[PDB]
Image (cartoon, coloured by chain):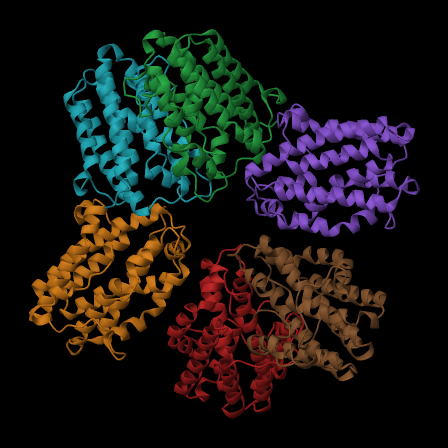
Chain colours: A green, B purple, C brown, D red, E orange, F cyan
Amino acid sequence: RKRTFAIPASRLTGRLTTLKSDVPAADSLFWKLWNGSLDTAVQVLQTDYFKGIAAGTLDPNAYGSLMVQDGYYCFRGRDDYATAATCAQDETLREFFKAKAKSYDEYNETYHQTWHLREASGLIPGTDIKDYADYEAYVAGSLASPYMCVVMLPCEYLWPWIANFLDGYTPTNSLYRFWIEWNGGTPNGAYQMGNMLEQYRDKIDEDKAVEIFNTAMNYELKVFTSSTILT
Amino acid sequence: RKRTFAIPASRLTGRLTTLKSDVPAADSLFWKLWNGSLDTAVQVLQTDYFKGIAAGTLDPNAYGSLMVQDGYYCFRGRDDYATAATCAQDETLREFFKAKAKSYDEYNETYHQTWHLREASGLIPGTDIKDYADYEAYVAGSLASPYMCVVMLPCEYLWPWIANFLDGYTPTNSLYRFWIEWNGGTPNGAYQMGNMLEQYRDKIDEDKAVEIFNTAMNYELKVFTSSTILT
Amino acid sequence: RKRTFAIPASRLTGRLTTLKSDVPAADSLFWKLWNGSLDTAVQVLQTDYFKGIAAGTLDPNAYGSLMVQDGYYCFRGRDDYATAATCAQDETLREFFKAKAKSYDEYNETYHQTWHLREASGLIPGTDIKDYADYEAYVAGSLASPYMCVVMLPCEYLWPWIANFLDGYTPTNSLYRFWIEWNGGTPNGAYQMGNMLEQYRDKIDEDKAVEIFNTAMNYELKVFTSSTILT
Amino acid sequence: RKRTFAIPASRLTGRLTTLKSDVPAADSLFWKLWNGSLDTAVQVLQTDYFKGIAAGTLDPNAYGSLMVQDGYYCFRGRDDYATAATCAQDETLREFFKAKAKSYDEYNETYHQTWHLREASGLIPGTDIKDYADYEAYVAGSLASPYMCVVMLPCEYLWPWIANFLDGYTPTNSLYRFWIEWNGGTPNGAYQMGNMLEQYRDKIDEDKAVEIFNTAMNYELKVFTSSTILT
Amino acid sequence: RKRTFAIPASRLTGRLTTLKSDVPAADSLFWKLWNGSLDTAVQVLQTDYFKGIAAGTLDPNAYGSLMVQDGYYCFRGRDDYATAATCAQDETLREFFKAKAKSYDEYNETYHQTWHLREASGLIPGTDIKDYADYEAYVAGSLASPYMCVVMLPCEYLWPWIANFLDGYTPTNSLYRFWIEWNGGTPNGAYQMGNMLEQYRDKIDEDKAVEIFNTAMNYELKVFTSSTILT
Amino acid sequence: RKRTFAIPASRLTGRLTTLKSDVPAADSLFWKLWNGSLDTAVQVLQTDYFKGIAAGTLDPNAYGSLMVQDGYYCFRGRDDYATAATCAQDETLREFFKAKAKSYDEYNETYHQTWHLREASGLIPGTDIKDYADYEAYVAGSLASPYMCVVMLPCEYLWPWIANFLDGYTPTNSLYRFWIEWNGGTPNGAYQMGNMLEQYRDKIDEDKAVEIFNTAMNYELKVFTSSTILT
């Protein structure tokens, strides 16, 4: 239920032994990326989806419809991390990506068990989630390894950020209060990936990283915007 | 998204031209079946699922989780009518089953489109819905044609009966009021199939028909009961 | 306040020493009778009276108006049990009926004390409650002793059944929640009378018993239906 | 069911032709009486009964229990006017009291019809309502005619005064809003009887009038206070 | 926060050592004054201001607007007590008034600190509060010392009286429930001043005292009536 | 009481004739400033103050307490524009600042009239609002004219931006819905001042402008944060 893709302490082995989950430093690429897309994050808060979460009035059909699509996304995201692991020549990143794929596998049992979804091929994605997933797959299979940390960061940081923002706007007895509880708290998975990414920032083009991060943030916005248009 | 599987007037052609959807007569097999399972129907009203619908407090995860499983069930149900048509004892029933399969195809667009489900094989059914679908497939492929009308009747009459019962218990401004609107009103699909069944009443063993209808009703109860157990 | 007409353990004396209040067996006349009237019970749940109880919106004038009439009914019901005791030649039934009259006397203090009602003759019954009470009196004074157990069973079983059904539909903080509390729980009085009746089932015509039980159930429905028509 | 005991225009004939229902003059005995008991009226507003009316949370058993007792009170009140007419000091007052008895008869249809009460003798009054009715019967049968106008005034003015005070405190959609609608508006019955009283003001001892009015007001308070004690 | 102007035990020194805060006797000038203005108090309860307090719907702009004006009033009231102390030749009243001015100073820190108000001259009073304050100042500076106890009594007794009246009408979870809590309880300050005043009742004209008290009560009503007319 | 400080068309005369209030271009200094402080704006949304506005539960004492301080701030702000006009580097800016002072005078009627505040000197500002006003006075009197446009922009854009964000989070029937209505819509005053600023962009140091705008934004945050601490 708790939505996290962090690598747990028990799997911080080998080259990952010293990987930390503390908040990245102010001058990190992680905060540079986030700060640059903050206008998009605010637009996410302005969607009918999140206004419905806070009010308790989100159409249960919109909620469920998006959950199925998020299953599709997460099934593919796990495969993207497996691809990134296969394609990495850097041993630390191979181990990191392999462990991230395992974290996705663990989280994804909610889709298999609670939501009765077998695999991505048994779903028909909407255009926006399909485009988003295809973009991530492109990054995983075609770009340098550290860009995978960039493109996957929005989905790991944005959701807790939204949850922590909406906490004080979502009454504890309201119907979608569970969304806050499942997603909110310290975004340790995001921070952990931010701390991994910082160690490779010299190996990538930061203007490219900005573009990739912004593009993924724009897809998050598209997905949430379209989620409540059931027409 | 009106939940109906009725054969529309435009498709009542050939052998089906004179098939009516008026309420079956009091002495029909249709009412004999329904009246004998009324204790089960009352227990469906006592499930946490329907108490949640009426109060507007059903967990959206329960609602969605069950909807995915109903997609599985309806995808299979369509295939069962295709099987029954292939096995049909006469041309009238072949046409009836083909028309029912098409009505399922039309309704099933909601599962493909709104719920993003491709096909039954891409879902992992829970035990109760799997057992139910397997039972319907057994009837379609192994028993005489008229028993298909019997086994498929509960899902066509029960849901409207529940909606119509709960209408006065479910406030018009409540979150799951849509359930009443989409399922309630005159159960013309059920009446239509009861009227078809009545024409083959002399062709079947009424005690076996009761057993089959009661089994399907019991599965509806089991499915609705298990729907809110997300453990 | 707790609405029960059971004979308490302290008055299970003499021939009644061994009378049990456990649930009657599945093959009992008690369940045969109930199962046969279940459609009527469902119609009772569809009345504006019970929809108002569950919603907390029942007009307090309708509530009170029916309570006065129920005082009339219960005053007469006590007298009917006294009649049945007088008219019984079977010693066990004489003792049973005498004890039931005493249970009615005890319950009826709520009408004398809380509702300020002196006796039936000081009230003007509505047509439906008058007809119902006259029917019970006819059974008591004109038919064989065991039919008195039949005709009085609906009022003892239906109300707890309704309360137990509506429990999960009636919020604990709503205005008529007390109705659930006063009437719900194990229907021990009904079961006890069912266990008495079973011992005489060989002495009556079961088709007649069905008719009597169904008629009383139909009166319950009439009374509840008319309760909210204050025009 | 507008609660009024006013003599309608159609019955203002003979000696009553010119009787007005305009607000009594500031210097009238009517206002002298009312103003002197205003502390009691304020205490009626502080009862649990009226706090329940305003909040919509008055126990329906308290509402109904008191209504039965008000039936007792009004059945007797009608008889008191009949007595006062028999004892009347002059023809004008005979006609006034007869007209008031008929207004009670008209209003009392609500007790016979909606509340199913036959007559006072079929009710068991609580202590406070019994004491109050006995006091009114004492005035009607033992004191000079004009004092009847004095003792019966509280029940005609207080209830509208309470309704009009609570109007702005009782939401239009609340369960006991009907109380405001049925009792509020212009207290024309009270004004009418005040205007009759004023014509006999020189015939009575104003200190005795104050004692009598204050006693009746104190009984209204005691009745409303005890109404919610269902112990 | 607790709105009291009582002199605390620690400042009951000198001539004030024996001053009590128990309820004044029934025959006191205090109750004579209050009883005579009770109709005005009831009109205060009928204002849109208090209907808004009880309902939780009072416009926060009306609430705040009046609070600023009450700061003005209380700033001036403190000065009035200082004037009364200066102008008193009776040593007990000098000490009393001096201590009352100190109680006002203590209460008035809420206006300085929470409401950011420096002094009366920095505010622009509405007509009604200005007239009220000017009347009090006239009494303080131009009439015999004991009349100061008379004119200041309404503001000390009326507010707790209103709070204690509205307690049972103001839900504990409603937005202005704090008003009840801050103002309600035993009106010890009012009683204390009533007990002081009783010792000088022989030294003033009680018809004049009535006029002064009634005039101040009428100003309270004017102030509350105008508070919600922001046009 | 629409909160706007825009110069109305009737006062766009002389040098101001062609001043527009259209949205500034994407490359303007206006948007550069705003975009750089967006993290602060998001933190304003996270204050207890705005969570209270959206929920309708903001303590009316917090609302009013802050309103008094905003009066202080606006009284001073008007004086700051008067100072800036006296110090103006050219005639166009002299006219602009004079027009802005008049717009403040017009708006400030709400503080004089509804809130009964005479002038800044009659208020005791809290620390944060004092610091903020002192900073604006420093800019007006000590720095080059165009920086006045920079420091005063946050209070003109932030409030509408907040209102427009919270519109979909604040129910139309909620107690502080008026806040959305009075502050929201098109921020034409802010756009107008941004368009004036843009004409002097070559006259200022953009890094200093960012520092100044960021300081004012940080003060808005501090003020809103401290507003609900009534300790």
Res D112 → quadrant: bottom right
Identify whether E21 is placed above or below B179. Answer: below
Q: Nearer the viewer, residue C187 or E153?
A: C187
Q: What residue sits 52% from the left and 77% below the top?
A: D193
Q: Position of residue E137 (x, y in %)?
A: 17, 59
Residue at 26% across, 80% down: E27
Placement of D229 over or under B134, stated as above or below: below
Residue pictured at 81% horizontal, 47% vertical: B33
User: Nearest the camera: E131 or B91?
Assistant: B91
Q: Residue at image x 48%, y 42%? A: A174
User: In x, y percent, where is residue B47?
Assistant: 63, 47
Left or right placement of residue B112 versus residue E76 in this view: right
What quarter of the picture does the C terminus of chain B occupy?
top right
Position of D188 compared to F44: left or right? Answer: right
Q: Is residue C199 above or below residue B54?
A: below
| Residue positioned most to the front | A14
Side of B207 relative to B4 (left or right): right
Looking at the rendering, which quadrant does residue C44 occupy? bottom right
Nearer to me, E13 or A218: A218
Q: Nearer the viewer, residue A84 or F146?
A: A84
**Quadrant into which the N terminus of chain B falls:** top right
Q: How many marks?
A: 0
x, y (%) of residue D180? Answer: 52, 63
What x and y, as percent, mark residue B74?
Answer: 71, 31
Q: Is residue F99 visible?
A: yes
Whether residue D145 appears in this view of the structure is no
